[PDB]
Amino acid sequence: DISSTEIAVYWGQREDGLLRDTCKTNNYKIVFISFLDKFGCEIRKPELELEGVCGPSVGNPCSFLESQIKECQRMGVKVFLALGGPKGTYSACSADYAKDLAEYLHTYFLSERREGPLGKVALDGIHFDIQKPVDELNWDNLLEELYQIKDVYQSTFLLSAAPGCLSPDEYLDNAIQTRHFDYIFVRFYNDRSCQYSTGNIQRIRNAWLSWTKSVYPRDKNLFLELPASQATAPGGGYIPPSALIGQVLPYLPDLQTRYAGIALWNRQADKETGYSTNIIRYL
């Protein structure tokens, strides 16, 4: 129901502050470290670079995040690595590369098997934020290879996706149809055909309905991804906290069986506006 709302947030920019401090707010249940945005056929070992935070150029290694990731996990926060995003050059390449990449993610990010870009860690999941890939092929293969690895090692990591609000999604439909993502974070912004607008929840309510009908299984596996300020969604979609709680959520079909919570585009915007703080106050 509404009271059990789980809040997720994207973190990865200088203005977001420290990961440790983000977790310590206790406002979030899931944090997406964002983004591994450069991979493809000839990139056997993808490197992680967070703008103004870590990587070759900020002269601070991303492996320094290891202890903060573990602190977050110890306090009950799930930390995911998000693939893709708004920028970069990313492609799943081919069926063979999909296996190579799935293995890479498992060995270096999901099992503490080897030292990777974020140190020796075992993240809670992998998030497919495939917004602007080179093309739509092989994302389903990547998901399937990670899913197979999960079975082989009887692992507990989660798999999630962030499609746009217009179904079927241009890039992730084939992957979503496998029914193998644990969570689907629908981006209800930057698309006038399926986002909220002042005094009109019909398009967003209808889009939510389209998603409940096309995503199986019928578990609590759907989240609404929303911008935390008007500035983070130039194409529209921002929903004031009071409107979300009082005018939108109560009117989403199958909220009681399908709704898991909300994801907020981005930590910086949330910090500036107090979005999650106000939502929490009203839950």
Image: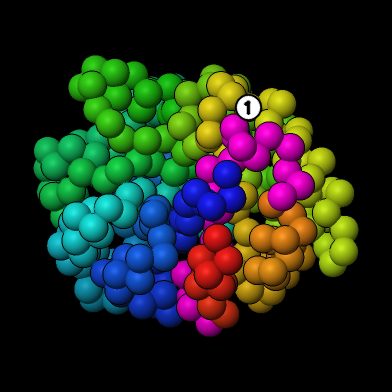
Image point (35%, 71%), residue name? 25
Q: Is residue 189 above or below residue 267?
A: above
All told, the count of numbered labels is: 1
Residue closer to the observer: 76 or 108: 76
Please state, as top left, top right, bottom left or bottom right, where the N terminus lies in the image.
top right
- The image quarter containing residue 87 is bottom right
Is residue 171 one of those drawn in magenta? no
- The image quarter containing residue 227 is bottom right
Q: What secondary structure is found at the residue carrying circle 1?
A: loop
- Give how far across and how far down residue 249 sits, in percent: 69, 52
Residue closer to the observer: 232 or 9: 9
Image point (74%, 55%), residue name? 248
Q: What colour scheme has been applied to the protein in the rendered image? A: rainbow
Please state, as top left, top right, bottom left or bottom right, where the C terminus lies in the image.
bottom right
Residue 122 shown left or right of residue 87 in the figure: left
| Residue 153 in view in this figure | yes
Span of residues in magenta: 250-272
- Give how far across and how far down residue 246 sits, in percent: 72, 61
Residue 239 shown left or right of residue 35 in the figure: right
Q: Which residue is mark 1?
A: 215
- Give how far across and how far down residue 146 sits, in percent: 36, 27
| Residue 104 in view in this figure | no
Residue closer to the observer: 42 or 167: 167
Q: Is residue 230 above or below residue 120?
A: below
- Give how far across and how far down residue 142 sits, in percent: 43, 29
Q: Is residue 203 above or below residue 103?
A: below
Residue closer to the observer: 107 or 176: 176
Is residue 263 one of those drawn in magenta? yes
